[PDB]
Amino acid sequence: MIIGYARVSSLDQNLERQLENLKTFGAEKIFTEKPILQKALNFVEMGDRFIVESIDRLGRNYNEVIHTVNYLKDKEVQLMITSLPMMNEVTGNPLLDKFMKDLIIRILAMVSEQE
Amino acid sequence: MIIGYARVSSLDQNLERQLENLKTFGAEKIFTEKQSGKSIENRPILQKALNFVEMGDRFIVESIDRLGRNYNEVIHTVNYLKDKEVQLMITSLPMMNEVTGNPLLDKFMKDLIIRILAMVSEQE
Amino acid sequence: MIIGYARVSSLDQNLERQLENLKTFGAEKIFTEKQSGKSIENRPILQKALNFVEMGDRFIVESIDRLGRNYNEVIHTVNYLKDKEVQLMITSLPMMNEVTGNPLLDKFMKDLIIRILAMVSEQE
Amino acid sequence: MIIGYARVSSLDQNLERQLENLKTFGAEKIFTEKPILQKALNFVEMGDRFIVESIDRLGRNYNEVIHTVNYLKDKEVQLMITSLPMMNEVTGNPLLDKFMKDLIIRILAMVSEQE
Image 1 (cartoon, rainbow over the protein chains, first blue to last red):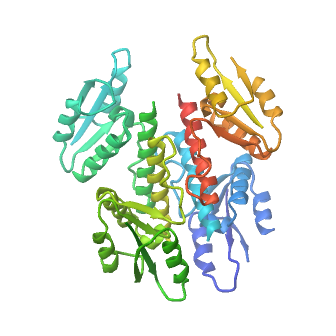
Image 2 (image 1 turned 135 degrees about the vertical axis):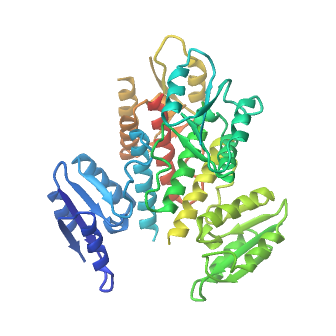
Image 3 (image 1 turned 120 degrees about the horizontal axis):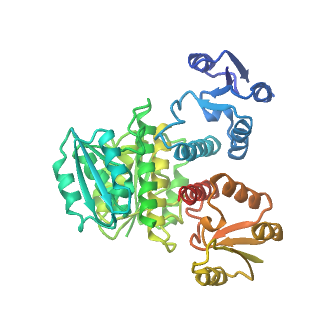
């Protein structure tokens, strides 16, 4: 199935749009956090899709973010970013696709951190 | 219309595959050249191909390396095609020109891919 | 000679730091602008700065985002500087223009970095 | 210290240049292979430098190559490629440096594989 994750840290953020975004792309359940992430990650099983609106939601730590993406990779859970649909197949050569996946994810992690 | 460009260094390279690839992705005409991808000054067929295409046409190759093995040249060629508003397609990269929602990311992707491949092709 | 360009959206941004950065990396003159990095048409100071620099000069900013928050524009500006043969430097990227042996890789690096940062700056 | 690794698979390759290359940049010892790699990796300790002439030497498998680079990272051994000196600091912002390290390494791994 399709699992969703949403985070906002402070007491003034447009959480609705986010949750509605996760809903938009097919999130049947959504883990919202203001360990919830842990729950989210331990919940997902092989064959599921794990979705966020953006990597910054997932974290703002290069190392950790990468570690988490690798965790999902290990568990064979499809990671998707609602702001990066089609991110999987940019070209049609799965190898290049994988490489680009990595790049994008890393550019984004770095951005998320540096902010 | 759809123009294709095909290049091989020798004849033991499977040129048929390449031509059939260009035909499949819609080549109405194919400019075929037996030559090194090291420069364009020694590639008048490429020149003909490029001068032939006009705004609204599609230009198709099997790989960037087919187009050349020189970063600056390849880049300049890609930009040349962009300026003339000719669609560059790479049949091994079928989903590259697919508008997938966010133009910024898309263009960024293109530039990136093309440059990586340009360098790859050159360094070899 | 070394020309610097400095931009801030408001005055609560630490403009002194930026100016001192440009001064340190050798700004003889600094074109200072209070404006959004969303476009150049509303940035005549940038225009003056760009027209001022000539072949042999250095153009220095603290960050690409200072230069703008528009991919195409930034890229076009970088290429503009390249065409006029003016050295673009980013003081936060001091070792970027350092010739480190392999020109191909170097140029590839530049293009890449600059484009990543262009997009970053835009998307924000 | 500085450890070197060199590989050639077949019976007709310019091994001299390679070994001399590893020698050039300061290789005190060189592991040459036609498990030797295992030896090379288990040999290096914290603080050492591990050097190859090129990533393809190190392998032609995206996954494995990456895994190995991560292994060296874990062990805090500096990886260097004699054809990519200065690769560490392209800009002067260590974060971006790390990111670029990753990129380059991956472009190269992909190239090494696809050939």
